[PDB]
Image (cartoon, rainbow over the protein chains, first blue to last red):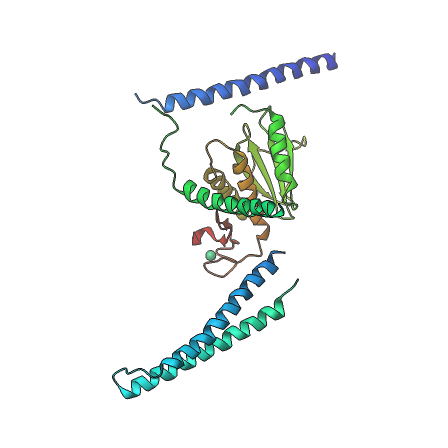
Length: 39
Length: 267
Ligand SMILES: [Zn+2]
């Protein structure tokens, strides 16, 4: 039971970390676009 | 070796100087005394010029003797290409320096994504040089690489990158535990001493200062070049006040582009 639950936890954390990195790159692009907007 | 090249060119100019100074002695003696209004003044001028010329001959002979004490020991197409290659290389170095000092580019506009393998290759290339710095990459949180740069028995720098571009740095002392309880890097800490908090501040200005827009290899290489100069902490005195200690601080400021020690109060 312990080993199965540890594997599920590790899968969830790898998914979250990769999500954070991709969202961070998108945030960088959006920050450049929004702050450098002329308006 | 290059020192023999410089000593030989030096002594070439020494012989030319000796020959011309001897001929200058005899040429000024050929003309004879000039007029120069006051009689006392003309005697003084002639004597002074003759004495100066003789002294210059003696100095040139002495310099030639000193270089003697210090001296050590189809085919034309290849040498012509060699000479022209060195000429083009030096010409291009000077012209590139003059032009990138004064660029006229105002904006990038007209009218980050990298494999982590590339980051490891770049940082291992930097770690191969500077034999007193060891850089140990790890990735505890995703693709953002975290670096421990140890530096002599002096520093441990924790550099937190983001896509092969330095983001944050924390400088701690040698003994200081940079690891947490679980043996991961302590990315968020301070260093219990005044000196290393000052060097964290100077390192953040260093990563704000060395900013090329596109190419990041020059940035990390130049940051490590600047960081390497901190090995003479606690040994270098300040180049403004001479002393080692201002308010109990060593000179924590290694100046960019001329790595000289200063207390930050001495700017
Ligand atoms: Zn000072």
